[PDB]
Image: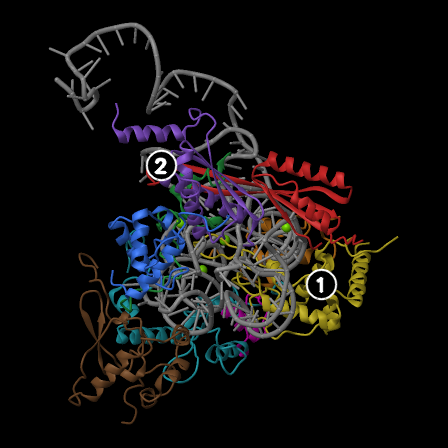
Amino acid sequence: AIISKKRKLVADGVFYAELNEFFTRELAEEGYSGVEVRVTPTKTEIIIRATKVQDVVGENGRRINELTLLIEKRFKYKRGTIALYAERVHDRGLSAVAQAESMKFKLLNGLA
Amino acid sequence: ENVWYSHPRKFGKGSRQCRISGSHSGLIRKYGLNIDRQSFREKANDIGFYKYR
Amino acid sequence: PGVSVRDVPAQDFINNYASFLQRQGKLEVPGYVDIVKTSAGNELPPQDSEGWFYKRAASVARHIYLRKQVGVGKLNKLYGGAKNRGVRPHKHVDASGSINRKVLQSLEKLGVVEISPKGGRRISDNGLRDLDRIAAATLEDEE
Amino acid sequence: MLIPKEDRKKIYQHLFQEGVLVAKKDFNQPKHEEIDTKNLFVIKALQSLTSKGFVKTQFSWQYYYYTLTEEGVVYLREYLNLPEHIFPATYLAGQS
Amino acid sequence: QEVVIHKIRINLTSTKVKQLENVSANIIKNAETFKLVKKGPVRLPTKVLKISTRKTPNGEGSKTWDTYEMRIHKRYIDLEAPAHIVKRITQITIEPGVDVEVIIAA
Amino acid sequence: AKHAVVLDQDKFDRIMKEAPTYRYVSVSVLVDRFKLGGSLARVALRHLENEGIIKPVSKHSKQAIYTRAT
Amino acid sequence: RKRSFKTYSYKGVDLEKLLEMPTEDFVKLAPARVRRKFARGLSEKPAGLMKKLRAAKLSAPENEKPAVVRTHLRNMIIVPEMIGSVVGVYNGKVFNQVEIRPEMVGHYLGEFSITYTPVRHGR
Amino acid sequence: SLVVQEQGSFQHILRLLNTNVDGNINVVYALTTIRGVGRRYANLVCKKADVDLHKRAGELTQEELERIVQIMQNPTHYKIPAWFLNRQKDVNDGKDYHSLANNLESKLRDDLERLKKIRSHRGIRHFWGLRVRGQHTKTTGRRRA
RNA sequence: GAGCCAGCGAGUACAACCUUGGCCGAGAGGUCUGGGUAAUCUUGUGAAACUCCGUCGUGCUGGGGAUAGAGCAUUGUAAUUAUUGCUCUUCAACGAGGAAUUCCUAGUAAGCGCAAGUCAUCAGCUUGCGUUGAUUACGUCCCUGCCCUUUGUACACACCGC
Ligand SMILES: [Mg+2]
Ligand SMILES: [Mg+2]
Ligand SMILES: [Mg+2]
Ligand SMILES: [Mg+2]
């Protein structure tokens, strides 16, 4: 902690990007679209927009918990200071990333 | 397990890898990015960097 | 009316100061006189050779008077210029630092320059008076 | 692969404690974060585990990520001894 | 009983500008409500982070460039106000995007 | 070398004879009327400006324009 | 006769002192680069090779050359301890035999080998 | 400052250190013209002598010339720092020295010979008739000695 | 010698960043000390080209600075196949460049330096920046390219065609 403000910002951005990439990689089955990061004091809110919200969740805190743990491991945080949430997307068709993902899935399956 | 498996790679092209590819080619080390330029370009918008002028 | 240091056209003032110094014969010699370049880029020592040093000192004093608080590196920067570095283009490299320091020391000894807080040096009262006198003289000459 | 078995055991224990593992993609690194073993060794172990099912691996951004499946968890338990109603991150510790 | 004014600077750094402005406004409103002596929202020079990059990966074709840039917006709100009040302020008025931060020590 | 650098009493005398005449005296003008070379010419000019004879117009380094009294 | 042609040497005096002055002295009486090198951390440079050289010197036939000591460390400087012994300076191919003399003193081992084969056609 | 009055004409071209000191011009310039003295060094010498740099100085005095010669000969005896020189630090354990004429040339030759004997990379390059100080002759300088 | 004015920037705490200010050193560069995570300190980055007074005057000259030799420095584990800097010395070609051909229309051209980028160390490079700041058009299809239209076509992998 304690760096040049600009530098800090850049770092944060990089972290966000990394997170996004991870989500893209990992939550393919779940149909992930995008992340929303809110860095308040103490807690940090990581909101996730995916299609299969239930899938993302697991069975009342499992997959999400694991993800959180992984994040903590990556970025030297403690338990409590990261808070994941898996939310629905308001209109999937308006989103582009989601659509792309769907298309990819279809291709994988083997469709015209 | 072997003793000598390390030249001193403190500094230079060899030490400074990127975050994504782990390359030593076109490495943006400005503002502590540490990103091969192509990679940065691919993600720049997500990392807050936008084209204006 | 009111006599001031600025009314004199610079170069003239400097010359006057140099003359005064010469008359005094008590600015004190460094030891490197004409076995010295004056800047790291100057393929020829001072053409005046004997003297010159006094003039430089005067200039330094004037600069100090002008500014709030000045040091050695800054002075060097002010002084230095372009190296005819070769077939390569010109950089800016700073002037003779040691020489500058010596000059400063001499000034201090005289009672021109005074040590300031924060950093560097400012001006003494006697020095100021001397400067004023010089300015007056210059004005008279002009008249 | 050539592991002093104690180290391996330690690694396994750590994994169990976690319910997860995050490694670098950095060979030549003398010792891992948290565990007092070589990172390379840990990575190798993880790879081995993956090869016999158990672990799920992601290689993103010079960071290997690892999570245990039910079968994997069971295997780990067997390796250890610990019977039932235990740590990992399959369920919460209390309220968090 | 206390009324111990430590003299507290709130920094407000961000990329998104409108949001930052809104936050500042909110802060000002809060201050007004609490009725304190404060210097108004001082705005510092917008530091721009420039990354010039050859558009190409392979450096083949014409030599075209892309100046990608980041705008940093940095504001200061200097409160001549107590500790408790400062704490309260910190507690209420937090938005996403803006980096709320307190110096506290004059 | 093209000569006109050698210094003499006779030469000096001829130079003197005379400051009077010529609309303007410029180092350049002096050389080459085939007189003493550059520096020498400058020196001569300076001398001429001691006590009247040739008064100045400009005063710059190398662009030193002087003219006859009075 | 008295003085043999002229002294083969570094900065002043004669040979008799060169051979018996060890390393520090040499450094003191050497160029700037050499001094700098000496100042920096010496580990593996003057250690094994030197020993080998010494051994060679010990176990020579007397009058004839010592054994050829092969060398990668072409970065090393010719100090006076091993004047006379033959060193095989490495050039990727070949440990090129370099004979150390009273004049080769205070120069690099690598600058007596030449890695490339020099240009032909027209000099 | 002053035009040379009086008869003048005191020797066009003087001979000094087995080389041609040119008449008129200036002492420094003359020194430079000698095979081995340069500009700054020449200036220094002049300063030591105590002659004006403004004077053309082919009408120099004999004593002055002698003094100059002496200066050229000896670095250490006079006030010359002894790291301002052409050569410095040479033979086994000893002193810094330099020449300035024919002498200088001889010294240079000797140095070259020594280099050749050593068979150092530089020496080798010299022998070849090539580029000692590692400048790239892939494009540049296509004629050579 | 003296005068002496910019704008883009960038810059470290797990490292070793920018580094003023003080002393040593002709320099380079050393040292002690700071200030700065930065409209705060470096930094008014008192950058150059410029302006003033003097020295050489149109001579391969004090223009020009190459190749050279030596030493002094620094970066790094390692500097010879000079990393770079500095100090002295050497003084080569070149008196505005043929056939050709590039760039340019206003704060432009050209000059001038700075600046970050790469970077342990190296700028003749580069992306920017400001400083100084013109000449000549403000047209045309002569050339060059490109575009259309009408024409002709044994071409359609399309003139490197058939
Ligand atoms: Mg020039
Ligand atoms: Mg500022
Ligand atoms: Mg010349
Ligand atoms: Mg380049």
Q: Does residue E64 lie above or below I36 as drawn?
A: above
Q: Given the image, what chain letter belongs to the residue carrying mark 2?
A: A
> Does the closest atom of ligand 4 sit within 8 Å of the Cβ of label 2?
no
- Chain that is coloured blue in the picture: D
- Chain that is coloured purple in the picture: A
Pointer 1: what residue? C61
- Chain that is coloured yellow in the picture: C
Q: Which residues are magenta?
A: H40-63
- Chain that is coloured orange in the picture: F
Question: Residue E26: image x %, image y %?
Answer: 68, 37
Pointer 2: what residue? A28
Q: Does residue I12 lie above or below F26 as drawn?
A: below
- Chain that is coloured brown in the picture: G
Q: Nearer the viewer, mark 1 or mark 2?
A: 2
Horizontal relation, residue G33 to residue H5: left or right: left
The local crowd at label 2, few if under 14, some if 14 to 19, many if 20 or more residues have their Cα within 10 Å, is some
Q: Nearer the viewer, residue I121 or F61?
A: I121
Alpha carbon separation for disc pair 1 and 2: 74 Å
Q: Can residue B45 be seen in the rendering of this structure? A: yes
Picture quadrant of residue G48: bottom left
In the picture, the quarter occupied by the C terminus of chain A is: top left
- In the rendered image, residue H42 lying in the magenta stretch gets the answer yes
Query: Colour in which chain H is shown?
Result: cyan
Question: Residue H46: image x %, image y %?
Answer: 54, 71
Horizontal relation, residue H116 to residue F44: left or right: left
Q: Give the residue at the far right of this rendering.
A: C1
In the picture, the quarter occupied by the N terminus of chain A is: bottom right
Query: Colour in which chain B is shown?
Result: green
